[PDB]
Image (cartoon, rainbow, N blue to C red):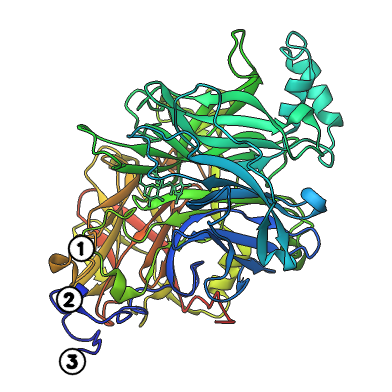
Amino acid sequence: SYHLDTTAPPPTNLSTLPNNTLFHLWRPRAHILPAEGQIGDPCAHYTDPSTGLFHVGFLHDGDGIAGATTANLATYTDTSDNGSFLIQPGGKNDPVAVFDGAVIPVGVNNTPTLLYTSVSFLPIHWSIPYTRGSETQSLAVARDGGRRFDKLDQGPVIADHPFAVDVTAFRAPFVFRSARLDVLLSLDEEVARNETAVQQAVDGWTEKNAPWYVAVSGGVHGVGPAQFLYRQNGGNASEFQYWEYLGEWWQEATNSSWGDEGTWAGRWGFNFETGNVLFLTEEGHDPQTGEVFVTLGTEGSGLPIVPQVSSIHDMLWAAGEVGVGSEQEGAKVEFSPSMAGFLDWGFSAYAAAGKVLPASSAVSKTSGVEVDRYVSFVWLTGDQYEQADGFPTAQQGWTGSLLLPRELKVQTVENVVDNELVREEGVSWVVGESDNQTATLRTLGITIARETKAALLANGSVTAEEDRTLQTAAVVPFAQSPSSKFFVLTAQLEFPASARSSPLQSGFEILASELERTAIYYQFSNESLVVDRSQTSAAAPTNPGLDSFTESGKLRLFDVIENGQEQVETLDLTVVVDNAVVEVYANGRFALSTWARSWYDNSTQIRFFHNGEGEVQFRNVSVSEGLYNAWPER
Ligand SMILES: OC[C@H]1O[C@H](OC[C@H]2O[C@H](O[C@]3(CO)O[C@H](CO)[C@@H](O)[C@@H]3O)[C@H](O)[C@@H](O)[C@@H]2O)[C@H](O)[C@@H](O)[C@H]1O
């Protein structure tokens, strides 16, 4: 007879416990996840034109797309009960499975319309032969306020992958509109070569009757990963049956990668997944003036290759330009990356699905936002993409969660010293404006959606810590630590120029007891925020299912001019700890999320950490405890 006692040592084998015994142990309170069961890819988000409510979707129990709605982008309500499903397999187009999809707010019958990957055969993986007809794209229309999606009574509207192309995958259609694409396709192939003519047409563009484009993710056996582009036939905004194939607007060589050493954006891998096409500005999303950005997941593998196994799941982002379709007979249009990085450096972060969130939305109206935004929902698989070594899934009763909604826009880093640090090849940023003395840098901006950040701190207990410096190695416990695993830790770390060349490691130790701790620090050596989980869980040693490997992401701190002097850019940290779900944010342009499954209720001390190498200044350190409930109606 074993009842859970989180103040006592964990049993040696967690998988021997009764189903659901671990249900609340690591479960978050402020994140998006079903009431129970497993959550897969986030997909099918859209602002309902009628109600202005923002709809969120996600695969659930490998049995279809489930959903929820929100009015504030802080609290959520399930569309229904018993799974809250919107659409499931079993149709003629989708006898085996229902994969990711995207929604056109005003589609068929002028109602929200879902274009999704209908599945008829399994297995499907880039490492094995593709079964013809495995993945097709079908339509379904929203009924009863989006609480369900009825499949149109006909076959798929894109019933096959490109003719005779040996695709490694063909799925996760994502819809978007683009002024630049309509122009490039509307103009002559000779007159669409000079930006002078283009830009002019781009200004007359009208978002309302523009045709929808569709990017499908996958690759080509023996050649490369790629995104397949389609658009309503003939650019007719009212054509929903036929979609003309524009070609592989973006493809890369098998297991190639941004930069020579693949340092800043992992690798393009063997297959591209759940692509998203964004158009940014310094303030939000604008399909007319925004720069072209694409977020995607890439499947990697070492050698030899393990059939049906993707050893690496990188959550990347790329930005660049779109031009005519070269001179050859390839794609009508091509996307050329200028920069690329990670949307989230977490091993278990993947399949992000975002959506434009209009200023006209009930969400932006209520919060006072008056610009169009692009909110992105990143997936945090719960069992390492189903490769976990015996995770106690039956015991937990649920699997996975989505990360906090995030705003994506163009973030600028001003007053930067245009130095080798800036002029490196294959990085996650481009020089905006430089006088060879100081330049502005452009990169993907990553922040917690404002309404969610506010809700996280609204009723939280706040406890500051005095600024302090550490030269010699030390681990200093905060004056006061929270008494629960639900909090937001904020701090700024100032480093002296002499630290770049040192083995310095500075940060914090969270979720700490004498038998447990989780280290989060910055390493100048490879320049990377690190989350050491080797001591995170007292239960991990005998339960390999609880992964404890190190997580880390590259974050460069540039030399800049602050008060009128040069200094190493301040490390601005924001760590949200949702019981076991941990998200590390840095400089409004870095994210590293992972699972920190601490066990003891006592495991809640926070400590300052410095390894004695170099010197670090902690400024403005504080903690907000409590966070909030994202599912009030449950
Ligand atoms: O190959 C065996 C495998 O086939 C099916 O999964 C295929 C596909 O799943 C994952 O792809 C994503 C990324 O998270 O998840 C959804 C599906 O749930 C896809 O639309 C999306 O690309 C993997 O990352 C891919 O490597 C994999 O090829 C099936 O669902 C699995 O249970 C298993 O049978």
Dot in front, 3 or 2: 3
N-terminal-most mark, 1 or 2: 1
The Cα–Cα distance between marks 1 and 3, rounded to whole angstroms, is 43 Å
State the SS at label 3: loop
- The answer to which quarter of the image holds residue 262 is top left
Q: In this view, does 84 lie to the left or right of 192?
A: left
- In this figure, which residue is indicated by the disc labeled 3? 1
Quarter of the image for the C terminus: give it.
bottom right
Q: Which of 575 and 83 is in front in this view?
A: 83
**Does the numbered disc 1 mark a residue whose Cβ is under 8 Å from ligand 1?**
no
Which amino acid, by three-letter code, is at mark 2? Glu
N-terminal-most mark, 3 or 2: 3
Q: Which of 316 and 111 is in front in this view?
A: 111
- Image vertical order of residue 50 relative to residue 137, above or below: below
The percent coordinates of residue 502 (x first, y second) are 23, 41
- Image vertical order of residue 484 relative to residue 557, above or below: below
Which amino acid, by three-letter code, is at mark 3? Ser
Q: Which of 532 and 80 is in front in this view?
A: 80
- In this figure, which residue is indicated by the disc labeled 1? 474
